[PDB]
Length: 139
Image 1: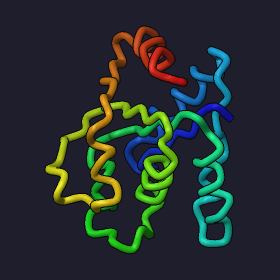
Image 2: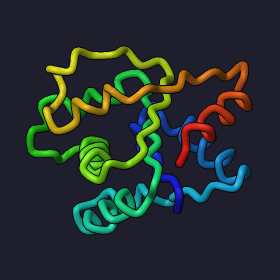
Image 3: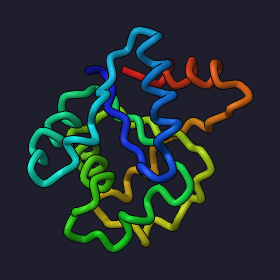
Image 4: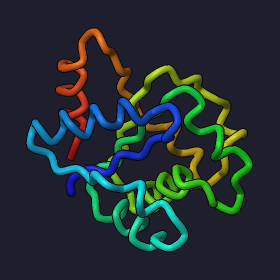
């Protein structure tokens, strides 16, 4: 698939579903059933999924990176996915949906760089125009 969407399940899942729907309707392939791979049993397949997609779309919902803080051992799935995307030089497209930007130093060093990728602000009022802006950022 062209696109891997990383998000925090308890705050970004509805926007993630909307993105999966509208990106596919616009002809971009997206990893759909990723959550089942976020288990120690399937970790290798999860990493390979991020590595296989050209585009890494990151939903930054409120508090989305909080579980990454002090996650020095990279046990958090979003943390793992971000580190994998950064490591491979993937096209990273953050989608901002209520996120409060933290100081980089509160995040693990291996993912602070994610904060340097220009994001797209989500707007429910102009959902479709926002989808078109996201597509313009995809490679």
